[PDB]
Image (cartoon, rainbow over all chains, first blue to last red; front, top):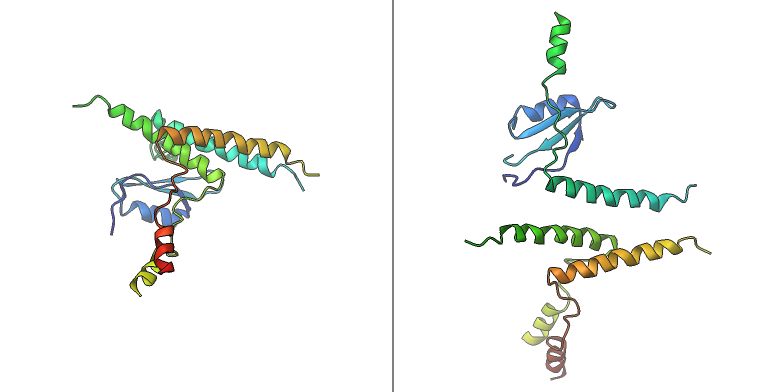
Length: 48
Length: 46
Length: 46
Length: 46
């Protein structure tokens, strides 16, 4: 178990999996709908 | 088919130059959160 | 104590410029493996 | 034969960008001297 010191590069994920991401971190993670593909980007900030 | 293959690589480089420089000026990318649309969607729902 | 603080940041930038440019020329960093020394160490042991 | 001729020139430029930037960070190139191998060669000779 390690704490991320600086924000990780965004990765593509499904809406169901990305909303889940938010349920753990939520101050520490960031998720957005990609308008064209309807999927979500998952970006882990510092402190994750 | 297209000889342009190295012109695709030449796009990637300045993107890195762009991205790195953008972080120095603290210009924030990927700032879109849940603020406006769903509230409007809630209003449009009512 | 030292006002040099922003001159530390100004070192980091070209390092990124250096590192990114180095990858383009395929100059390989962190190439040291187990090749010479231990064989010599084995020879020096005998 | 190969249209790549200007892509050879485009390699040279960043090399200059690489070399110039490398001197700023005081990263030393061409550091290999007589230290290890001949001593090992002397040991391997004995």
